[PDB]
């Protein structure tokens, strides 16, 4: 499944875009 | 859990922000 993460997608996840949540920018990782 | 949806969060979900994925804007819904 895909998740919003800060600072970055972790090992085994790939970045597909970004999220805005709680006034901050997150990586959208699947 | 939270998900990115187009056009909008559905009944029983609340919008907490947005996602950018595949060149489009999505609602971030929890």
Image (cartoon, coloured by chain):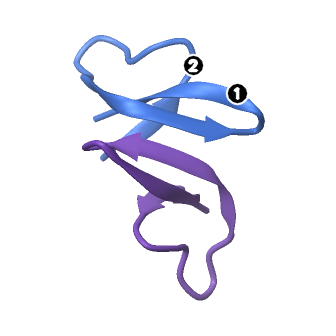
Chain colours: A blue, B purple
Q: Is residue A16 left or right of residue A20?
A: left
Q: Is residue B1 visible?
A: no
Q: Is residue A7 visible?
A: yes
Q: Is residue A16 left or right of residue B10?
A: left
Image quarter of residue B12: bottom right
- Provide the chain ID for the residue under circle 1: A
At horizontal 42% and vertical 65% (from top left) the residue drawn is B5
Mark before the other along the chain sequence, 1 or 2: 2
- Work out whether A5 lies above or below B25: above
Residue nearer the viewer, A19 or A29: A19
Q: Position of residue B27 (x, y in %)?
A: 53, 60
Q: Which mark is residue A6?
A: 2
Which residue appears farthest toward the bottom when viewing the image? B11
- Work out whether B27 lies above or below B20: below
Q: Position of residue A24 (x, y in %)?
A: 70, 27
Residue nearer the viewer, B12 or B7: B7
Residue labelled with disc 1: A24
Image quarter of residue A11: top left
Q: Is residue A27 left or right of residue A7?
A: left
Circles 1 and 2, Cβ within 8 Å, touching? The answer is: yes
- Provide the chain ID for the residue under circle 2: A
At horizontal 27% and vertical 23% (from top left) the residue drawn is A13
């Amino acid at each position: 499944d895909c998740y919003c993460r800060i600072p970055a997608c972790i090992a085994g996840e790939k970045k597909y875009g970004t999220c805005i949540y709680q006034g901050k920018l997150w990586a959208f990782c699947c």
